[PDB]
Length: 303
Length: 303
Ligand SMILES: *C(=O)[C@H](C[C@@H]1CCNC1=O)NC(=O)[C@H](CC1CCCCC1)NC(=O)c1cc2ccccc2[nH]1
Ligand SMILES: *C(=O)[C@H](C[C@@H]1CCNC1=O)NC(=O)[C@H](CC1CCCCC1)NC(=O)c1cc2ccccc2[nH]1
Image 1 (tube, rainbow over the protein chains, first blue to last red):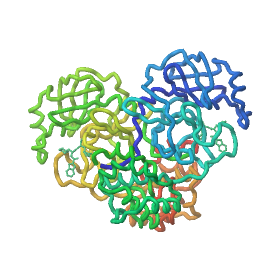
Image 2: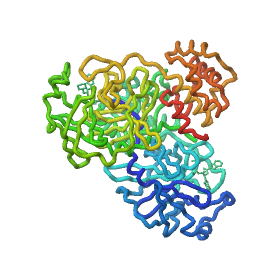
Image 3: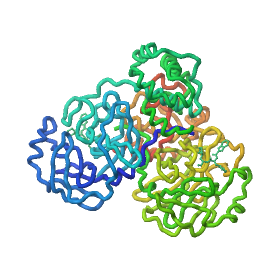
Image 4: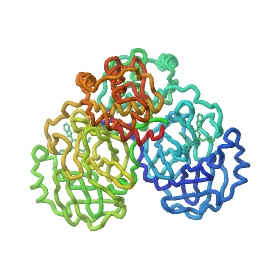
């Protein structure tokens, strides 16, 4: 029993983290085979953060301008190139700790683990969701750029996020490992800001199922609703619409608990219209939306 | 910016996890140098869980009754002994991945990271506090026994918890790595249950400071209180008393924010008597008590 925000074990990613320095800027890089991946804004000086032309900035660089350090061993850079908003630094040594890996872009509402790093040294690991507005609510200080987000399946690491910047509201923006930003954000200085966000409905329903599996039942009721009537309520409370595919994805949890999805939707409707009346669910006084149905199944396998 | 429940990177502990089987019972062990540590209840059969005599059960065992597997390599057991509620299985190979380590017993109100494991394979990592009643609110299924809790300081792992059992309320109980239980719990079948718990006041104040550092200020006020008047309120709301040592420990966070500790105590008094009036702090609608002052400083270093 119990239900925690749980990250994947981070050792396979720890063995990939390095430090990259260009000029006076230090951030992290990801070393896989003989390539180190990092944010291209490592090459930007304070004097040209408004409208950097990265193609020009990079043409003016040589391999020796990039200092890469893996633990206390310097890696020699033997090529450099840009891939969208990431740099690829070819080094003369393949990482002996390279795990099986993939580069996968995730969807809003999906979750992943972040290994926060500074100076190429891992500091902490935590779980995050990609919000509907393509930001993440992370925990990142100066120096954390190049830290990555990932999921692990069997022994394969699927990297899905590299950190680039913090927006004015304190949420975070970055790219996939092909260097393409999540959301309408750019690696230059603007007034860019997080757009309106919404709550991830299917995840809230998954977490209510987690709660039932863990013995929290007070929010259940004898009612059911139709999908259309539920989505009218969802729209009123800034929740994403629930689709039949979402209902299908919740099938296993519904079977395990014996509570039909539209029955649980009636509970969620009542929680949105009435609140919790001083009670808690899985130790929270808010409806939690950063657990996917797969996260719940993985963690609450057989109660 | 941002504030997350963050665990320590788990790779140094991943390299220590093994599987231990005795009879039909499989759980996890911790392999350090040439010793594997695991819960002694691995030797208990279903027929003697009410009043096992572990001294007798172990005298009837031989080394070959213990099957230890590290990845897909079997380790040969060459000695066995009991240390309080842990078994020590001497094996014929020193773990080449042994980190620098210590065995440290923690205090209630202290936090640590748990590497949940099954069949000697790490599954997830999360942060936990030792409650005042010496339970932990973990996430553990069948097979998780022998999973450990730890903190990391520089490159030294301080192991502080090994998992043994779940209580009837769904919270968890275990030992330090010397095999001594946290709290009034035993590794035999009884009606034992978690005793009354309380909220960790100094941790709530630390988290309010984290919130201020992260831009949540709505709960601040112009008032201050005395320590005695605050502790009268604490007692009414089942909070631990706040000591002058706690005030001293909060010194750095108070200096960084410019908010005196007894000024923040006045805010906490108002939150306990009035509630939050529909607002949130660091994404929570409850007062959070599983971050220590050190956790806050480590994560919110320089905003
Ligand atoms: C890389 O390590 C950091 C990570 C920041 C630091 C604080 N918290 C984080 O996540 N990235 C930055 O500091 C970027 C660097 C820019 C260089 C030029 C191209 C764009 C990225 N800057 C910011 O994250 C930043 C600047 C800024 C100014 C005003 C409001 C918000 C804001 N965010
Ligand atoms: C080891 O892997 C497990 C971990 C449990 C499983 C479910 N969640 C956990 O944390 N440990 C157990 O199953 C113990 C084994 C006992 C063997 C004999 C000596 C004491 C431990 N049992 C329990 O955790 C347990 C049994 C039980 C019965 C009734 C109410 C609660 C309860 N808890």
